[PDB]
Amino acid sequence: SASDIRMKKVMQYRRALTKVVKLKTHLFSETVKVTCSKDGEEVQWFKGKSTAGAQDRKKPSGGFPVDKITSVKSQADNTKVLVITVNNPQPTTYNFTFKSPGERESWQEQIQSLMKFMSMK
């Protein structure tokens, strides 16, 4: 079932999108915890110490719809830097930066798969 498989599949991506990463942009520069909504419909983050809505994390410190991500890219050298831009919400470009030279890029490719999964063109 296309809905059942998606809802389970987004949960698979959800774990791979649930991470700790430091954002750096016009938004702010802070260490945030990233993740996605239940249907994988959104990308969400928690800035430092947060209050995950009702323990089920229904209260993100920020986020945006996955379908609305206008571009998912990596920097030119992108050693520890990621670059993601969104359309529909106020256009912001999120730089996912982490200590691990792998963690972020794992996120980079994983989000793409999730994005193209539900936002398949």
Image: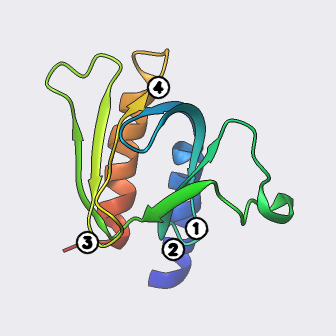
| Residue located 31% across and 51% down the image | 112
Q: 100 or 12, which is in the foreground?
A: 100
**Disc 1 and disc 2 in contact, CB within 8 angstroms:** yes
User: Which residue is the site of mark 1?
Assistant: 8
Q: Quadrant of residue 121?
A: bottom left
Percent from the top left, x then y, of residue 113?
34, 54
Disc 3 from disc 1: Cα separation: 17 Å
Q: Is the residue marked by circle 3 packed among few (<14), some (14-19), or many (20+) residues within 10 Å?
A: few
Residue farthest along the left direction in this orientation: 76
Q: Tags 3 and 2 in contact by the CB under 8 Å rule?
A: no
State the separation of the CA atoms marked 2 and 4. 26 Å
| N-term mark: 3 or 1 | 1
Q: Alpha-carbon distance for marks 1 and 4?
A: 23 Å
Could you tell me the amino acid type at mark 1? Lys
Q: Quadrant of residue 61?
A: bottom right
Marks 4 and 3, how far apart at CA: 25 Å
Q: Which residue is mark 3?
A: 120
Residue denoted by label 2: 5
